[PDB]
Amino acid sequence: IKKAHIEKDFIAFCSSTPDNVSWRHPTMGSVFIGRLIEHMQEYACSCDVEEIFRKVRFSFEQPDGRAQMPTTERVTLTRCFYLFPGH
Amino acid sequence: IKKAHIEKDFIAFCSSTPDNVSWRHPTMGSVFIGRLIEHMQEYACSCDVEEIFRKVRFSFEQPDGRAQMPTTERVTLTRCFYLFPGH
Amino acid sequence: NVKLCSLEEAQRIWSAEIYPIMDKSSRTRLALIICNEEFDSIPRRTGAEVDITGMTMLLQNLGYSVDVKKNLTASDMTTELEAFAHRPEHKTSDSTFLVFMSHGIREGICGKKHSEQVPDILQLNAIFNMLNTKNCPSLKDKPKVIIIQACKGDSPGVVWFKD
Amino acid sequence: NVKLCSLEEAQRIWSAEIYPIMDKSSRTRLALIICNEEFDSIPRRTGAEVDITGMTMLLQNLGYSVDVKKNLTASDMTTELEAFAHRPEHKTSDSTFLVFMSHGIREGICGKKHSEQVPDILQLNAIFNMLNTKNCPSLKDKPKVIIIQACKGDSPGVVWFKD
Image 1 (cartoon, rainbow over the protein chains, first blue to last red):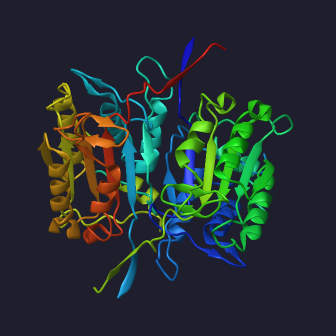
Image 2: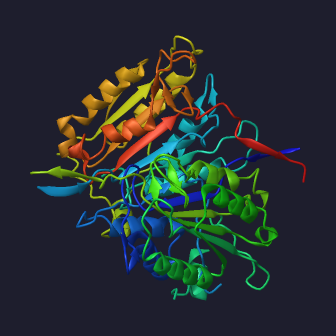
């Protein structure tokens, strides 16, 4: 028998910090989801997921109006995950 | 009065995954700590902390002997943290 | 809808610290979206259809075969996640995406039956467990991306300051 | 002991997505190391002195004034963290490092008095709270790096496979 890590190559991206609300527009949808889609569309070609998620977090930097701060959690990615869209 | 995010610009780096052990040599010290120091010494000049931590995780990839997998947790870094050693 | 990575762009990225991507014509990428919109004791999540649409289109355009499940209890979510982890296509896949969208509290994600009196909660811990190396060996060494749209509690998440 | 970032290397890195660094001659960077080596009910953490030495030397060489605290209960750790968060030097600092090294369980980091019967645990949640924007306004918008050497439970963290 051979040994393998029980938990590896995970990344979680949540819409807000622990204890805190995430916002959803009744007609335009969830802000975190919309922001994530836009950044994935733009940066999947050139950035790994960790970088993209960081960029998403940056977009929420200014606590204007309905503030929230997306969080990356339980990261065991050992390599960069590039999506190579088109490949 | 003005609003500010309650939780922002944090990164946690833990020695193992939830539920799991981290190892420490009685004379050579904790493996995670030793590995972290070596990677910080080498890559602080050229990589941001998130990248360095990912590199540290990679070094533990092979579950040889006393296996463990360091984990990044509760990341709200909105920008890259470069240490710019020497500056 | 996704800006493409050119051949020279992919060559610029490619060395030994990148997740390997399987051949386009032979790979079977899978993704799962679980979205709760209608609840027994919590107001309807109007706009969730916009979220499902966008995430489905994006993940499909990134090469994933997307399955969509709606209005489930935590137990149903558990059963679905267990079935998803057992899918043979993961063996000929290089990665996966798991998308959860619902009401949420500190403890985790709300199932359709959730109440303050009778909790119906899927814990984040359980999601990781069901997708780990033991319960999902087919995704060993492969990136598993978990996306969660939900509150993590009812606090507005702010502190006030004068100066 | 740290490879230096050259002027051209720093120019190569520098655009609007990097944490700003304060002037070398005017900045007052702070770091804290809490290390438990001797316990009431848990075996001595031999080798911890090697960890303290290395982390102290590294953090000093990265420009941090390092404070070292040894063999504390969770309450003592809490008091020390509260005092650390209140340090005026953070106002003229651009970042901080918090290093915790001890025995650990699922719930968190063990204080020197920890037992299965009488728990002495510092929760990770509490560390974040004590260093957040409310309790530590001086480190608002500044990177806070938390390093924790400890078990997160007693499992070897592996699954076995034949093939």
